[PDB]
Amino acid sequence: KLPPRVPNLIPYVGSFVSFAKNPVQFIIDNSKKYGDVFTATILGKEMTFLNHPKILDTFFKATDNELSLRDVYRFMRPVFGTGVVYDADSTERMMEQVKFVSSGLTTARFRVFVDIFEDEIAHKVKELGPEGTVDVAELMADLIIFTASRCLLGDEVRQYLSEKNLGKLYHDIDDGISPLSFFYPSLPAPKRDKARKAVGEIFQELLDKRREEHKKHPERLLDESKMDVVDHLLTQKYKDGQELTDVHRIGILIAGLFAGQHTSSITSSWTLMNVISNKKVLEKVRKEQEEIMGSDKVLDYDKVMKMDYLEACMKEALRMYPPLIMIMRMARKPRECEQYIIPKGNILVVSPSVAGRCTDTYTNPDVFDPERLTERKEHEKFKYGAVPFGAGRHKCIGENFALLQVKSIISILLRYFDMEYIGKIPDPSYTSLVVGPSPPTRMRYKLRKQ
Ligand SMILES: CC[C@@H]([C@H](C)O)n1ncn(-c2ccc(N3CCN(c4ccc(OC[C@@H]5CO[C@@](Cn6cncn6)(c6ccc(F)cc6F)C5)cc4)CC3)cc2)c1=O
Ligand code: HEM
Ligand SMILES: [Ca+2]
Ligand SMILES: [Ca+2]
């Protein structure tokens, strides 16, 4: 029959209050009370939490006409744009648009991306000086504004960042997104909308300029190392032959940038903080760096590909502090889950955060221990033991780019600086759509070469 329910505090509002304090502890506590599968009413939505790795196969492999992503993420429409990704006309159109972004994330582009990271960090160290203190979360966000933008859109974007305040516009859009919008997609957000329109105008101009650059220098279209997402959007069509609109191209780029920034800056923050705060982990990370770097003075792709221990450190931060804490779908048909049937219209929920603290999978889950993955392989105990990037048909298409960006940034920063974190590693703050550490996140730095 139906899964057990979390008793409602009030009708309609349901369990919103305990939920919004800490959605992760809400799921944990209620798992303990009600088991692997339970339902809560939350601001009018029937939400059915799936809380053990064991049962997740049917969730991750269902077709979009059974478990719809578009029904639950459509709320992002005022950020991304009408007709884009989860507001696309169909599952099919969404998948095609996602492929246009994946199409600028090639090996050839990754070799160039390393150079971009080196270049932006070198600019940034001029601000930072020989020593100081800096907020970790801000530093990473600031770096990734410039790196993600240039990686996805090309170098032509940088003059807008440097001269037309584009980075402030991003913040205006992105602080304009409340997680509450998931329940109330029509919440007014006029500052967000003003900024989104401004970025729209700038990106329209970037498209217009690229078009005539394609005329002046069509060889660009033949060089895989110089082809970016803007180039692919300007020269591709849907499979059925329908051309894209410039409004669709703008929205895809904004969606791509949004994806390319927040989850990465947050992950590089939690990763760096935990690395520099743990003497044994820092030793190993630096020993690995010194071996891979050898006599060379700058990074390249092949070097990053060898940073296995640093990668493990990132995965361990992803276990502990996954930035997307809830993966959702709407049930378009009733769904069997173990002994239960989950009603049509219910929203099924999987939490990477809950999974990462599951003590059936992880021993001492509150401890940052990259060796739990590299030596003890604790993630491998279940097919869905670790799902920070999703799984199945909708698994993150950005995973390798995020790995590259975060490993590269943390590698280059280490090369430049000794760094120590000030204070206790914070708790996550659940006030934002993409979850990051509670501010402030400060560290001291000092340059390693006079
Ligand atoms: C602050 C007021 C406060 C008051 C005081 O209570 N409050 N306090 C607490 N709560 C509260 C807390 C939690 C919630 N829930 C938490 C879960 N939320 C949620 C839903 C969907 C999300 O999906 C984002 C999609 C998936 O993938 C992305 C991202 N991405 C993928 N890779 C890289 N980036 C993506 C994909 C493709 C693209 F191309 C682009 C993209 F971006 C976008 C993320 C999060 C909603 C419900 C609700 C309310 C409050 O309301
Ligand atoms: C550490 C960084 C990141 C994490 C933790 C992350 C996590 C996720 C997760 C969980 C999903 C699955 C959402 C769902 O099934 O409901 C996802 C989907 C996606 N991510 Fe990421 N992501 C990261 C970086 C990126 C980057 C860099 C990009 C692009 C440049 C990107 C683009 C996407 C896209 C386009 C999807 C949609 C796939 C689909 O619906 O078919 N992500 N990511
Ligand atoms: Ca409650
Ligand atoms: Ca779960």
Image (cartoon, rainbow, N blue to C red):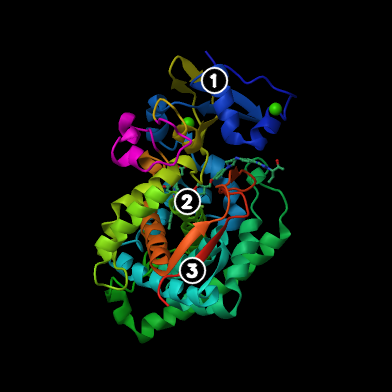
Residue 222 drawn above or below residue 25: below
Say which residue appears at 64% left-offset and 33% top-offset: 19
Q: Earlier in the sequence, mark 1 or mark 2?
A: 1
Q: Which residue is mark 2?
A: 277
Residue 144 drawn above or below residue 30: below
Percent of width and height locating residue 70? 51, 43
Percent of width and height locating residue 126? 51, 78
Percent of width and height locating residue 102? 37, 57
Percent of width and height locating residue 45? 63, 31
Disc 3 crowd, CA 10 A, few/some/many (<14, 14-19, 20+): some
Q: As rendered, which of 401 and 292 lies closer to the eye?
A: 292
Residue 13 drawn above or below residue 217: above
Is 365 covered by the magenta stretch? Answer: yes
Q: Secondary structure at mark 3?
A: strand
Tags 3 and 2 touching, CB below 8 Å: no
Residue 19 drawn above or below residue 191: above
Say which residue appears at 43% left-offset and 83% top-offset: 212
Q: Secondary structure at mark 1?
A: helix
How much space separates mark 1 and mark 2, taking CA atoms?
A: 32 Å
Image quarter (top left, top right, bottom left or bottom right) of the C terminus: bottom left
- Three-letter code, disc 3: Lys
Q: Earlier in the sequence, mark 1 or mark 3?
A: 1
Q: Magenta stretch: give its range.
A: 362-386
Tags 1 and 2 touching, CB below 8 Å: no
Q: Secondary structure at mark 2?
A: loop
Q: Which residue is mark 3?
A: 446
Disc 1 crowd, CA 10 A, few/some/many (<14, 14-19, 20+): few
How much space separates mark 1 and mark 3, taking CA atoms?
A: 46 Å
Residue 32: image tag = 1
- Three-letter code, disc 2: Ser
Disc 2 crowd, CA 10 A, few/some/many (<14, 14-19, 20+): some
